[PDB]
Image (tube, rainbow, N blue to C red; front, side, top):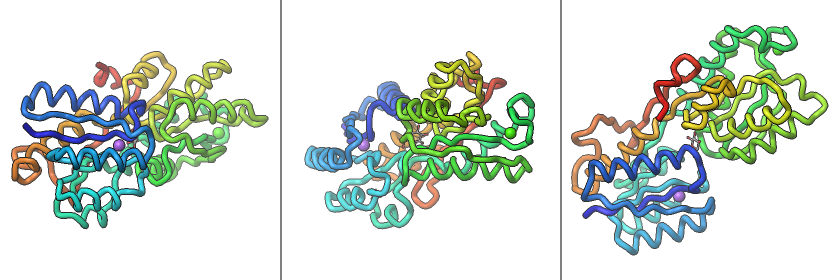
Length: 307
Ligand SMILES: OC[C@H]1O[C@@H](O)[C@H](O)[C@@H](O)[C@H]1O
Ligand SMILES: [Ca+2]
Ligand code: NA
């Protein structure tokens, strides 16, 4: 058999929970010779470090690692190298220097700039179609920004490029608030409650979140005070598609969890068997990474992605 030691920074992360289910299913359906050892790092890099050691000692064929601390890539790769076991990092990108430090390191993820641009496009379309969104009539989008995880490039890229896209198309924006909620619905709900209970809550026209999980929390907060505000996320998790169906979210951006899970399995299968990681697959490694594209989602196409 081939054994993959797979770690997830925490099990309640919505997007990664979907990917974990996908990987389990694909492995069962297509790879009878692969065994998955799944690990929950409890949002602790120290727990992850110990888990990596356990998996090394158990002699897994490939380490498949999701960083807890998004800056800890070099240390994790160093452990794999010292153990002489190949490593595929996923979802939290350790950067090129770290990947280049080990001949048996690879990465599967995305180019989050592209998701920021798509989110901007989704917002632009909805904004233009709904003049009522512009509550103060100034032509400017007064927004709040729910930022994900500091140091995880998906967060800064979605924050930067969504707004830059809008401005590039001649749509003025004004940031009323921006705060960190770490991909988490409950944290986002708390932040949104603070914003909606503030003296100037009325100024908010658009809610932008770096992921769907935080958008879910924002929606709970908005519903409680009986307001109607357009909310945008990223991932197209099923819960968000349902909110779009219900008219409680306006848009998101599909992040392809199934494709990422498939890439991890296909690359790991090759790596474990002395084959070039992309052999017999659709994937291209650019600077040792697979970058799986995103898709913009709104009321007009969300049905295509429901399961
Ligand atoms: O690093 C974990 C995060 O990764 C992002 O790509 C995703 O949009 C978030 O929902 C969360 O899963
Ligand atoms: Ca306005
Ligand atoms: Na992990």
